Amino acid sequence: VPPHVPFELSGAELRDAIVQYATNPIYHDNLDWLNHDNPYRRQLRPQVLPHLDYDKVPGRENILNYASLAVQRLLTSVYEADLVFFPKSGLKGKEEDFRAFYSPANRALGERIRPALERYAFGFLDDEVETWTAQSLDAYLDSLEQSPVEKAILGSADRERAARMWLVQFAPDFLSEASPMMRNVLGYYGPAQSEWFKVVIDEGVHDTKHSTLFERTLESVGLESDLHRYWQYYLNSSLLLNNYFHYLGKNHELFFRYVGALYYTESSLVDFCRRADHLLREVFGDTVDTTYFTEHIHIDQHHGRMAREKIIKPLVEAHGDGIIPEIVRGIEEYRVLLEIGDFDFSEQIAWMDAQPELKKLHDPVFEGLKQGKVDAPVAHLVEPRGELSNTHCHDGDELCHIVSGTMRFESGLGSSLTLQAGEGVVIKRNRLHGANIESDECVYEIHSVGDYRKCL
Amino acid sequence: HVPPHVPFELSGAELRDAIVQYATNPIYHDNLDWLNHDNPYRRQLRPQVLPHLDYDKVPGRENILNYASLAVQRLLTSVYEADLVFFPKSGLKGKEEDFRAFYSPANRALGERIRPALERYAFGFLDDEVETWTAQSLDAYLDSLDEQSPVEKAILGSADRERAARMWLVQFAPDFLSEASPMMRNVLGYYGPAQSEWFKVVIDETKHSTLFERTLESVGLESDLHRYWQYYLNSSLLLNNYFHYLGKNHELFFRYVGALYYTESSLVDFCRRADHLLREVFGDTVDTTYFTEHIHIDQHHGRMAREKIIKPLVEAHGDGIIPEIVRGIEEYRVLLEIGDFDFSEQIAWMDAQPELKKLHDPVFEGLKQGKVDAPVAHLVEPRGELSNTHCHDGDELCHIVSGTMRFESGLGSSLTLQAGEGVVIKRNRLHGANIESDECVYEIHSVGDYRKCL
Ligand SMILES: CN/C(N)=[N+](/O)CCC[C@H](N)C(=O)[O-]
Ligand SMILES: CN/C(N)=[N+](/O)CCC[C@H](N)C(=O)[O-]
Ligand SMILES: [Fe+3]
Ligand SMILES: [Fe+3]
């Protein structure tokens, strides 16, 4: 038997493999803000990927940096090669893209880089979450206010816009509802397998399928339900939460983490749906369809009790107390990700609402640079009409200054500024944004100021 | 600027090395026993032979029961099954290291890198075995689809009916004990009304795996995966793997739609024959509930598949998908033919062991007359060196010089070979051996066609 060479992929070889995956034409920059009923095109900004360091895994303070957003986008695309999608309008005329996404090559290239991407995406959780007995576990589960999202949306300068931005964050999860969970039903194991399957079944009648109900919610507020129309408006943290469940479902060494996360999500579901129904009704009035959420507003309309009694209990008995720390870890990791999502979304809404003031704030920041309060690297850019900078973020504060021409500066769904000669905008660290050129040519500068407040 | 795309490429020595890399995980090394003992993480891939196979030369149908094809089928089963959840019947306690060796980032990535090449090797021949359509002509075709069956003939014609039937039943263990797992692969995602129709079929599969457990146990077999790994025929793995292939690779979704229609439409006849044959072989003691769940004509999802899956998909996605639907049906039918042949051949081979032990004498004598010039391998193996099951691409003569060998030809099919004895080993037939003396000295003569030595 030849010696086993352990799997290894790092450094330049890893960078090249990531670029190889992501340079498939279906991943190149979109010329528009939206994907138009084409579930095979996902914007991975492959031109930036050669310049990121995938070997240096970020901690929590840096997980909203651009490299993390880039990796979350990559991971979503890799996981979704296992999911079936067809366009709403049918496959006719989209066969080439279908075959580009579902190909032996696209799968193999993505699967080769998946281990490194998962370390980059989830490695920080090792430091955010810390032997057990059946006794300790029972106490723990037993021990488990206006929410951050409610505050963000209800306090917004534009409540309807803020709520629409919120709703599109759920498109990949709710429109493919239960897909990551279904990954745990394949195979051959104990009575717990049928219990898992029961939960999945709840999430074959198409009209009552929960994804169909969420389609109606989106359509009732003027949004569309084709995946991934709103790709460029998906926040880092939203992708992270969705990806976490594909991670747990695909990687069966993490099965017991999923068991924990299932218990916690089912136990929290009714409160989540009640709040969602209330908030949406307050924002949109009679016209919003909240049936997706009201399917679970009755106190017993969840699978939490069954998860504890028919999944956790039999698994601990069968497989021993060694699995308990994994159950707890799934719960605690998921709770960390929820915190990150609340922060990221709140920050994004504030950033969208502040655009007029951040356009004005360009003036004193630009003046500060002239006075030499900060010595800021400058990038000088010249871009033609319709060069659409697909959405991204930067790791420090940046000042965008227009020398000549006209730019549409995009900060969120329904959140835009028109920047003309001599105008600009303060771009806040980690905030999702993009731009398009509206004149024949636009000449502009990006100044890397670090902390814009030092220029004031 | 966007860097140029380097197309995915893996072939030649790099591919061989990658296959060996995957398969040298300790959980894949040769078993010291004939059976896996309630450990679903250990699968025998005979990694020591893998460096010497040519994965670039894709076999045609005449060669798909050759050893390289068996080796690739074993590899593919293991690669696909990393996506399936298994725990031991006795629980995970004491098997955690193997659990983590199978479900690891490395094991998955190594298997996925080689999956494209393995699938070309496994299924490439179908391109030449199966050859624009309209909704009209598809209807005519489906309408045109339809005497002991080959399996009935093989089992009821056997020298040992109970043994033949047990050998048959273990072939289904990976499929039936994980029932509907490959089909479940098609329900993930977001597509039309057909998604919910697919899901309904999956739901419809007491859970059926539990019923098959009872069938196995009623005839003295065990239901832990993969106890009987070394007795799984090439063709059985091929049939199971085909459905994981269709389910994992969504460019093949429409092939799966066709294969679903055909399997549902053939299910009742299959189950009726299985029930009758098992009752004849075993009498009152066999539990056939797994099969009698589907002995009623038209009580399958065939009509729904045609009206609620095929029809809406053709309307939505166009007539371009129709040839793929047909191809799934025709490919599956080819694989069934191969399975019928392979299983029939294996049962005949098991039943003929006493004659093939006697036939060693004239074949060995023929080699002395100078009838065939045959390459000879001279082997010396200690007690308990268990040659995990495999096959050869030509007929081989095994001759024992000294010591004692258990020569294994199938489940419950064994010969004891002593000094001066041996056996004719028929090409493509699954077999192995164990050494029962302190040392056994023996010879393998590559005779090609043993009949030329007579
Ligand atoms: C308004 N521009 C901006 N925020 N940039 O980061 C520069 C964009 C540079 C280039 N068009 C791209 O998409 O990378
Ligand atoms: C009875 N022996 C036999 N049929 N062989 O092919 C050779 C056995 C060679 C070696 N033990 C192996 O497992 O490959
Ligand atoms: Fe930018
Ligand atoms: Fe042999």
Image: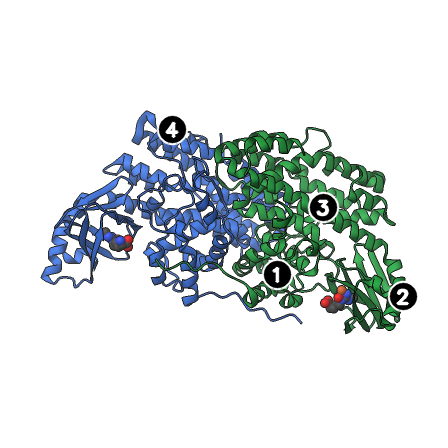
Chain colours: A green, B blue
Q: Nearer the viewer, residue B448 or A279?
A: A279
Chain ID for label 3?
A: A
Q: Which residue is label 3 attached to?
A: A339
- Of labels 3 and 1, earlier in sequence is 1
- Of labels 1 and 2, earlier in sequence is 1
- Mark 3 is surrounded, within 10 Å at the Cα level, by few (under 14), some (14 to 19) or many (20 or more) other residues, namely few
Foreground mark, 4 or 1? 1
Q: Could you tell me how far apart the alpha carbons at marks 1 and 2 are, in whole angstroms?
A: 36 Å
Q: Which residue is label 2 attached to?
A: A364
Secondary element type, mark 3: helix
Q: Which residue is label 4 attached to?
A: B287
Position in image of residue A42 (x %, y %): 66, 58
Foreground mark, 4 or 3? 3
Disc 2 and disc 3 on one polypeptide chain: yes
Specify the amino acid type for callout 3.
Glu
Q: Nearer the viewer, residue A402 or A290?
A: A402
* Residue A292 shows in this picture: yes
Q: In the image, is the residue at mark 2 within 8 Å of ligand 1 by its beta carbon?
A: no
Position in image of residue A246 (x %, y %): 60, 48
